[PDB]
Image (cartoon, rainbow, N blue to C red):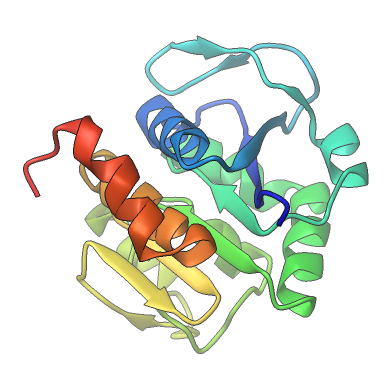
Length: 189
C-alpha cells in the first residue's frame, strides 16, 4: 500500500506556522509532502519574515499530481496570492472534480471562494476572515476550531494548526496513525 501524498501551496505572505505545522505533522504521519512554491522554486518570504525554500515550483509539482490532499495555508497576503492565481484555480478545480480532499486554514479558505470551490459547504476561517469568506452567502459559517464537510476541510488560525494537521492525517491515514503521531507532540489535548 503506497503512501498518501500532500501538496502544500506556499505563496509570499503565507503564515509560516500554518505552513510548517501541517508539513511537519503530515511527514510524521508518513505522508509524502511536497511544499510547492506558487511563484517558482525560489525562497518564499512568509508573513512574519521566516524564509522557506520550497521543494519544487507549483508548475513542476502539478505535473507530479494528483495528490490525496491539497493544503492551503493562511496569512492574509498569502491567501490573496493564492486567490489571484490561475494555477491554483486549476489545481483546486481538478482536485474537486476527482473528489479529492482540500484543506485550508485561517484566511486560506477565502481562496476557495475566489475559485468557486465547494460552494454549499459548512466552513470556518479565522474570525477576521469571516466577512470575506461569507460574501454572497455561498457557504455556511462554523465556529468549530476544525470543520470538515465531506472533502472540504477548514480551520481557524495558528492556534488550531495542530488540530487542522491531525485532522488531515486522520482523513488520509486513519485515527490510529493520527493518535500515534499526536502523542510525541506533547499537545495539551
